[PDB]
Amino acid sequence: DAVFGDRVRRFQEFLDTFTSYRDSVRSIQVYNSNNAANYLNILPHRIIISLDDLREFDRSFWSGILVEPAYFIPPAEKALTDLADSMDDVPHPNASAVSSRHPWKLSFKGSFGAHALSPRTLTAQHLNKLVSVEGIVTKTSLVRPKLIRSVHYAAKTGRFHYRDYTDATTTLTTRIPTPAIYPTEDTEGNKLTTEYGYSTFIDHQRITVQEMPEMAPAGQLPRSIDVILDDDLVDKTKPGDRVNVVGVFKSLGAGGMNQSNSNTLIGFKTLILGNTVYPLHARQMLTDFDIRNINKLSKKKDIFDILSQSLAPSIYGHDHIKKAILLMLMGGVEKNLENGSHLRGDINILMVGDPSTAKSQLLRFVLNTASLAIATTGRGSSGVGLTAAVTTDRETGERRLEAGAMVLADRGVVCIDEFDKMTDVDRVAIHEVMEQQTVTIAKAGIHTTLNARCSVIAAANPVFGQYDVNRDPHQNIALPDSLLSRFDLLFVVTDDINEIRDRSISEHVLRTHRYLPPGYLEGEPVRERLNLSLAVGEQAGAKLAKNKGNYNGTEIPKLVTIPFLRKYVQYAKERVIPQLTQEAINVIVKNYTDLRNDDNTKKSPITARTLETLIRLATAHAKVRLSKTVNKVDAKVAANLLRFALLGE
Amino acid sequence: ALPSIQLPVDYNNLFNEITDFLVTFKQKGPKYMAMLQKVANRELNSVIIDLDDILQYQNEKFLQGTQADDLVSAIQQNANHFTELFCRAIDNNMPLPTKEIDYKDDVLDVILNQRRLRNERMLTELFPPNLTRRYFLYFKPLSQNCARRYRKKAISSKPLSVRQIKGDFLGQLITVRGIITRVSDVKPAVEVIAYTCDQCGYEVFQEVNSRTFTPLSECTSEECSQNQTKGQLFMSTRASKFSAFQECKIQELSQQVPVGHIPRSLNIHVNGTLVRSLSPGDIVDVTGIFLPAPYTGFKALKAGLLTETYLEAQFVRQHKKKFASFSLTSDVEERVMELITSGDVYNRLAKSIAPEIY
DNA sequence: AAAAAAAAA
Ligand SMILES: Nc1ncnc2c1ncn2[C@@H]1O[C@H](COP(=O)(O)OP(=O)(O)OP(=O)(O)O)[C@@H](O)[C@H]1O
Ligand SMILES: [Mg+2]
Ligand SMILES: [Zn+2]
């Protein structure tokens, strides 16, 4: 009755108290006006409020929102729409577009306290309450528009009529249902023609979010919940993404309380009307002094060795492997030609060795430190299901392709373990990807080519239990040469027994195990921790807090932390695209001619494709030092690394 | 019942301006009378409307302070309504045939003449105009240079991707781009359905624009309207009016797909003389009307507000390339003369296939 | 449509 007006005026008072939101709204308005008629982006009518200030202003309204949003959000939205209408000033508007009536829906950020849950923790007593849930995106539905309000016209009357339709998921408050019956006749029988272009249609999509399997009870499968979101943010993110979704958790449907029930045990349906979505990413933007520090480090002489040594400090030796991983994470550029079609741009690395030489651990480290990566096991995968699958959507009743493991890793890196133990059939499915970086699906009436430009890193064991240095390299490796020729670098590792190395590695490994997490005692095991205190988060250059990287002093050479290295990778993969020059060309051609005509035994045969590997390695090294041109030093280091990987020191 | 709202659009002035444009337009005299004259002589089978002509006519008549509004904006905002406005304007201003007609072949007109000589002799039914209509109406999207000619942002075109089409583009005229994959066959579609009345006066007609259809049971014939039944009404195949119907779907190009996604599709309906103007496996620039389609055909009683959508074709630019089956032309004749002058050819042809391979 | 167990080649 009047409580709606009371809440509306209180929210108007609160909006008038804080002057940031008004500035944002008028900025949106002026940008929208400038987009209209000046020689393709438009800002949506959505604003995000920080409920910390609301709590500091009025505790009653804050509690009402966080406990029963159904009776508090609509008044706030009405007040915001009224403010926007009052402040707006358009003297000559349009006809069809003026009847949009966007209500300026809201988004929230700030501390939630006990209302930040996980998909398993959602229970009965959290219904009808605003919540924020973390999780992983499992699968999505198709974007389908839905009607809101229809526009009708009658020729005889000349008066435009309108009828409004709402559903259970359309509004927070339950109202009397309305069918989709089109009004075609007037009260006096005049004919009504539906007017497209004046009616209102809003986009609709359903997604399902799953709890992270890492934080799960022992011996329990992960559980998932479904989220409905509409209008804006309709097609953000994708399956295989870590998200934080804030919205209202409410039930819907009769659920058998009508006469349709067949058995006693009938349960209701629960669903979340998502209000906002944030990318978790376990942040992604560089600051000014960050760029200053990156430039200062890149102008140093020996940045590349420092960066290589910084990777996985708990692994002894394998320095060239670390350098190869560093060059692979930020490989060369892709080439396209009007007549030359397409040229591959990145690097793939394969390692083979006898057991217990720290390959899987390095693979896990590469998974953890990469921008985007997917873990795959040879035995626990099927090639047909690795690329694409056919699934029938429950809503639309049609069958649509579901993205496979490798497609999700587009512009990423894929790590495969037990590669030599992986079925031969599915191997061809890999080779196709290694051929043109594109998978073709022609099955059940769907003919589509899907882009997959990822890099693949794998580690495999030799045919015997241990490597035989006296045998043919082809004899020791079970994989056929057809796919082995694709990999740019092949590495063979062996645990040669030497008492000096044995003592050094023993001391190192014992040093690692004598570690204690900061601020926690040694008498009790590790305990799980809660989420961050802030549900949604966000003097320069004189501190160098984490810029220098050296957390602990152990050697004269420097070190850098993981976040700074990742920021360096993000900057390098975007801001620099080097161009090769003839000075490095001479060195590359000379060393290729020399290596080809050395005429001695070697691990693998060499052919014309190795020069492409040299070119992209030089490009990657030019990217490492952040230069737009390729110097002969990059050619020299690439040749040295190749000689090490193929001859051995 | 239904609340009423006020809109700045009124169709009276729009129709008057449409008629004035159709009559007075100078590009042979007026062009839009030449097309109507060819249609009257049963020569032209479809009518194409250029929005650039309307825009430039309005712009050049704006120099005199008589014009008050613009039409192309309302065309872009809504399209289906202007189709029936245009067909009514054409039907009102159809000139007489200046050429002879082989009148015996038009069996529809012969049957209608027989019905008229039956009914009007007694001293008759006013048949719907679309049954009498023989032509098809098509629109053509404007060109960007014409928009550049003036200050206004009358742009349209802009061949959006399949996934770039949102729920706010329903009812507008939009242009899409993509590869055609599936093309169905050609099948007739009903426009006006006629029933015979078993020799009981006039034969009842009906027109259904929906995708479903229901038949009649009783008829308005006077002796049939008499208190006892006189003959069961039966559908007549000859008297009805049909139209060619075809459907196809288009897929997004691989260049426009965002990373880590699966391309989407779009359904296209096509009717009239434009049928069979496209083949599977080509890049096209299709312009049409983006219309909603009811879900009730599936008959699931779900998705109370969710609906399916489709595009109705209006103009197709086939684009891509043409094989032409080496059809002889003058230019290629001078080309082969140049080849004759070139001397020995096959060595250069071998050198010129794949220079990238050494 | 796609994964998993069984007997015969
Ligand atoms: N250089 C090293 N530094 C630290 N730990 C090492 C090193 N070499 C081996 N290890 C240890 O050896 C153990 C074996 O690990 P892991 O199984 O990942 O190795 P691997 O060589 O990939 O073996 P596999 O062929 O069985 O997969 C690990 O606990 C790892 O810490
Ligand atoms: Mg291992
Ligand atoms: Zn009868």
Image: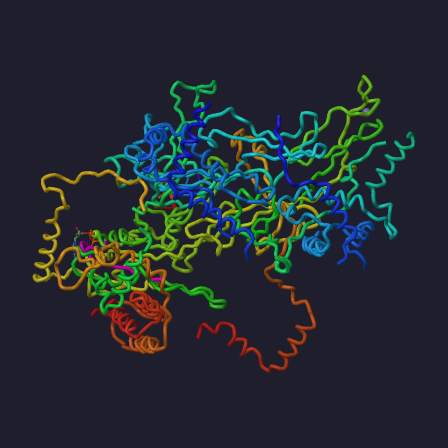
Q: In which quarter of the image is residue A94?
A: top right
- Quarter occupied by the C terminus of chain A: bottom left
Q: Is there any visible trace of residue A392 in the rendered image?
A: no
Front in this rendered view, residue B143 or A408: B143
Lateral position of residue A153 relative to residue A557, left or right: right
Colour mapping? rainbow
Relative to B60, residue A614 above or below? below
Image point (77%, 27%), residue name? B233
Residue A599 percent across, percent down from the top left? 27, 76
**Residue A384 magenta-highlighted:** no
Magenta range = A346-359
Residue B35 percent across, percent down from the top left? 78, 53
Lateral position of residue B145 relative to residue A175, left or right: right
Q: Is there any visible trace of residue A281 in the rendered image?
A: yes
Residue A304 percent across, percent down from the top left? 24, 65
Image point (87%, 35%), residue name? B116
Main SS type for the magenta part? loop
Residue A187 percent across, percent down from the top left? 67, 25
Relative to A436, residue A5 above or below? above
